Amino acid sequence: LKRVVWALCFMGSLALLALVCTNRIQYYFLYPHVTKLDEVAATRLTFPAVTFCNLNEFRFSRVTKNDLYHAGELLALLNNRYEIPDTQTADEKQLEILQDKANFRNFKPKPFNMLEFYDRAGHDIREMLLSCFFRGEQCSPEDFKVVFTRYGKCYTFNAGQDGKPRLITMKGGTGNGLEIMLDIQQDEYLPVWGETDETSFEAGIKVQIHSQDEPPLIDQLGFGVAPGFQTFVSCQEQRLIYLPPPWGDCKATTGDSEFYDTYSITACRIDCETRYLVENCNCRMVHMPGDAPYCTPEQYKECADPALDFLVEKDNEYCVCEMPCNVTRYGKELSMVKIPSKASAKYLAKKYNKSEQYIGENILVLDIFFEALNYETIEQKKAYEVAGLLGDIGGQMGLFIGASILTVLELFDY
Amino acid sequence: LKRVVWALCFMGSLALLALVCTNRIQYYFLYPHVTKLDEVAATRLTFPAVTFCNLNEFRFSRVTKNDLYHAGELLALLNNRYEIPDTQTADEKQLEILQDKANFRNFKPKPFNMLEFYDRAGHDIREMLLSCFFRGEQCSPEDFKVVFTRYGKCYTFNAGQDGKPRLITMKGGTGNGLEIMLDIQQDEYLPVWGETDETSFEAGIKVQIHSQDEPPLIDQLGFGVAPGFQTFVSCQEQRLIYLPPPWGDCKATTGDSEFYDTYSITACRIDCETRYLVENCNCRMVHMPGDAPYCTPEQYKECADPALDFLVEKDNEYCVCEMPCNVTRYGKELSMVKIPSKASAKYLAKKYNKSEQYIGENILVLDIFFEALNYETIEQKKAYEVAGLLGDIGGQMGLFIGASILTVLELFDY
Amino acid sequence: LKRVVWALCFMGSLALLALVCTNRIQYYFLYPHVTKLDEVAATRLTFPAVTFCNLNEFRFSRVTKNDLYHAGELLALLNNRYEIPDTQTADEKQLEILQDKANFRNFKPKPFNMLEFYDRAGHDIREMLLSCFFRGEQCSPEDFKVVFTRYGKCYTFNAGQDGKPRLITMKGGTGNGLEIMLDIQQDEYLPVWGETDETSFEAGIKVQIHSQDEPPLIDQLGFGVAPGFQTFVSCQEQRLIYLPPPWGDCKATTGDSEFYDTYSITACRIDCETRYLVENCNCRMVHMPGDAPYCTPEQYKECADPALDFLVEKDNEYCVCEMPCNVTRYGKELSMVKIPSKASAKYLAKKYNKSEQYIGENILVLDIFFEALNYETIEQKKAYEVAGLLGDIGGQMGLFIGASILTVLELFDY
Ligand SMILES: [Cl-]
Ligand SMILES: [Cl-]
Ligand SMILES: [Cl-]
């Protein structure tokens, strides 16, 4: 009667238990994850490395007759007949110089490679750096490590190598970071007579803020700074931590991955770009690692350059990288004020033995610091551990029928 | 004795179970949610649409005597007596022109509407676009779709309509995005003699980056770009996914919502603004959808303009929109360098048949790209599913008393 | 036989239960937390306070002979012998003035304090503010509250004090925020003849956006705005809510913490900086709270200034603050256009009785507003409540052995 009528109700209770338990178990086998995000004002924070590059790759006063011979075409300074292009943007003063050192009448070529050309004619930290201060202490060129990029001879402050103890940061604000005054030296910019990958229409510098153990990709990922301004960059360190499989695609940062000691997206890209250029050109660009021969100006103009433009512009399948397990991103907010003021133009002009207009067209101040909330963690965390699954399917087993693994295994037998 | 003394302890065990189970069940009926945030370097990413507008709405050379007659007051070029205001910012060259075409002695008005005025006098992509490149390929005006905003005749790159396959992006960096050189043509800016909603004190352009299926609100939400700089915009695609009720207020993006095929905040605003202007003015602005008649200059000056200023400035209750279930936000970091350099000014001047000063005051380069971590997901996820509640209240039922639904329903009866 | 052979299997079942239950209980005693992040288009949002400061601290026309006597050395206008430094950046017009009022032949010093000097010579909101509009309504200096910073006499719009109902914001876009036109008055900038903490090489202003009940730290945390541009700041209100111990280090915002009614990182810093300066100098700077005597120019130059530079640059242990439970951060995206255009330069020049060049070097427009997704919540939430632990260890107890607290306590006794 009523005792056996709610045994069918018991059949319904079993029917329910089936759907709910298969729910929590499919949910387990989706491997769901959630996010733990903590923005905080840190302490003992490690100051990142700061790489910068002048937008003019070579110095007009340092280009020699041999430099002009080997590389004048790459720089659009000579046509294919080793002469000044008749379609040149004449300057009565500059053109006299160039056609004086473009006179190869008594000239016999001498050995030449691009790395020495960049290292020698590239802008010099010792005459660009007008002022550097970190947390109240003044820097020198000794504190900037020479690094070569596609821009040429570039510099990294707080590179952290050289056994030099990396610098730290405690609070937020300008006084707890870097400030540098620079002269971009527009009077040393090479004439632009055509368009190549080595000349530019812009005056200023390129900057990129990165981990000490992450290489720079300043050509693609950096930001610019204009002459005649003071730029404030308020930063924030964002540490991103991902889960390995099966929860997500994530590569161990101690990656057994060629040219660099640390695995990062940028390093993976530079690796592949190097393999690609060596493979297709038998030639490496000045900034690439490895041991291939550096490209000659003809190899730069004909093979290496379009190879890299292809990799960073058109390629969709050859070169793609995985996500690491640890990634460091730097949020930033930029801001400008004008330099110099009328009250100070004559002061700066006098101090550096330069014209007032020159100061207006070449001088530049850069402040790099962190805000109050200077450190941020974005860590992926597992959302349904196996134990919580067993405890849940357990409260579900016990709910509708009050069974156990003993009751089943024992009752499945006896 | 001791057997019946811990039956009171059993009463305490029941007392505990009550509070804990009512805890997990109230917690269920709060409908709590958490967040799943994944910043990643994507692939096959869809490039957004990029809308831009010159800050000068009309071209001084294209304003005709009929255009000046109908609209000269809206542009503060004529007072209420159809004449040059005596309080004009005289220019010996410009004033001769305007008062030459403000001579209505032999003039009889001709038909006129604002849409044709904007379309004709508005700046032209074919003479502003000095250079466009996307991922190594050069663009033409064919790649820019004409869109009308409150600025006038504006343009959208990669609008994605026209059956043109939307463009994709793979890596981070400048080479994997758009770069355009523009001439803002300050020599064609109309004289500003007063303050209206059609004239501006600033030179440059306005830009807004949006989904192909999200309309632009460039007047309110866009950013500016100044002449004489190259601006870098490092972007990041942020996909935001919300939960529908009862977990949150969230509107289905396939919204059955008038003028556009997709529901977005911006489209909802443009919808309501159109209804409002039609209702209160019997008149639609040139950029609004629907089928009302376009406003005459008198309707613009007297009714439509203050109506829209009211909606976008003062309104607090008439026009408010819900949150969609899918939202696309684009993070961005801006950066400038100066253009032109001294080395290149004469080059650019020669190439475009323009003065060096003109190049300094009108020329502008814009790079739009993504960083390495170019894609970000912010998805709301349910925090306490019903199954996990039952499994939990289950481990709680089994803990203190070891009961089941059978034990109760059966014991509640027999 | 087979009945007693799976009692050893029962021993294995117990072995499993031990590890899994000790897993969920250690997990409980790690006190894990997760994050609830909601970016939304809000309504009835409270507009923050906006503090700004001219980069020139004193006005050259307001510096009197007594002001020059007491403070001329602090400003690098006089050497240690109360005379013009022979290494001055001469200006035939300015130098006549200064050496006219540096003539102390018939001068006897008069009482002097830095607060009155700042208040009097500091730039005036009533002659800098050329235009202010909030949500369609125009502002006056009445809407700006005077606040003193290390820059001097500064101003805060929508300070929210004075019983003035704080302003609200509804939508995203320029029309739903503040726009102001300013003259930085480079013609009133004091000559810079040396480097001190009161003079600057830059022209423009400093801005900081903060809660009405959070003090400004504009020297360290603010951003700059350059003359000759219109700058757009697209903002986003981010409310961060942390967990108190034992889940995290977090201080109650109703903090019983000295000089201010609300606990914030900035207020904690200003508190400690004040204690430090009073302790080490018997002296407070003009912008610090409390009741110590203000510093004399000699105390500024010799003790107070290097004390604060030390605190904001070098200090690593003396002054460090805890994290509050509620923090308000404002995301922002900046953007510039040039001002004035050629079409409008003469207009603005005429309107304000100023030269066209002056307009180009001193005039500045600032728009502060929010984007569509104008409000963001980042709330830490508990990840494993005690009830869910008991329900889980419960489904685990019931799973392997089907026990209960009664079964144990009763069986541990009888
Ligand atoms: Cl690559
Ligand atoms: Cl609206
Ligand atoms: Cl401090």
Image: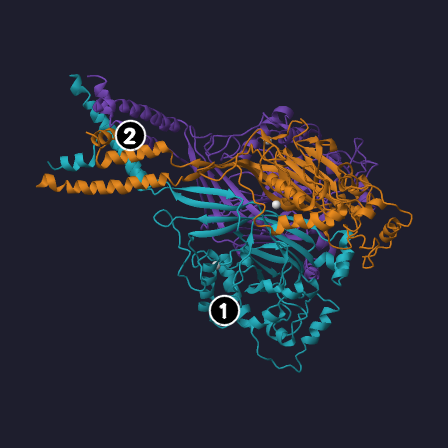
Chain colours: A cyan, B purple, C orange
Query: Chain ID for label 2?
Result: B
Labelled disc at residue B394: 2
Using the rendered image of the protein, determine whether residue C119 is visible from the camera's viewpoint: yes
Q: What is the quadrant of the C terminus of chain B in the image?
A: top left
The residue nearer to you, when weighing A282 against C327, is C327
Q: Residue at x 44, y 42 (%)?
A: A36
Image quadrant assignment for residue A400: top left
Find residue C328 and report its horizontal and vertical position in percent.
Answer: 56, 37
Badge 2 local density, few (<14 within 10 Å), some, or many (20+)? many
Find residue A321 and report its horizontal and vertical position in percent.
Answer: 43, 56
- Viewed as shown, does residue A49 lie left or right of A345? left
Q: Residue at x 55, y 68 (%)?
A: A301
Query: Chain ID for label 1?
Result: A
The verdict on label 1 being within 8 Å of ligand 1 is no
- Viewed as shown, does residue B132 lie left or right of A341? left
Give the foreground label among 1 and 2: 2
Using the rendered image of the protein, determine whether residue C355 is visible from the camera's viewpoint: no
The residue under label 1 is which amino acid type?
A: Arg
Q: Secondary structure at mark 2?
A: helix
Do marks 1 and 2 share a chain? no
The residue under label 2 is which amino acid type?
A: Gly
Image: A365 above or below B94: below
Q: Which residue is mark 1?
A: A284
The residue nearer to you, when weighing A125 against B254, is A125
